[PDB]
Length: 42
Image (cartoon, rainbow, N blue to C red):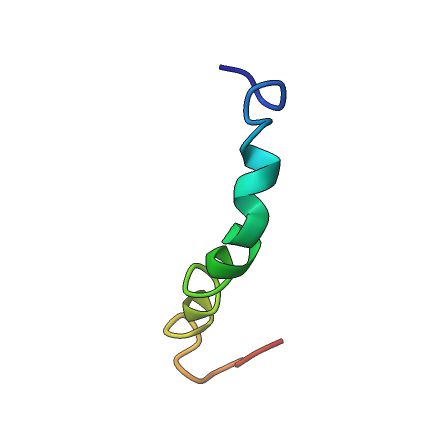
């Protein structure tokens, strides 16, 4: 187990979509609730 020398081969890959599916639901939603409709976006 390492950080890059390991994660490599898949890590940089995984992100293939992660950066997308990861941002969606695992970020977007994180925009709701906490806001409830206050400071809203930004």
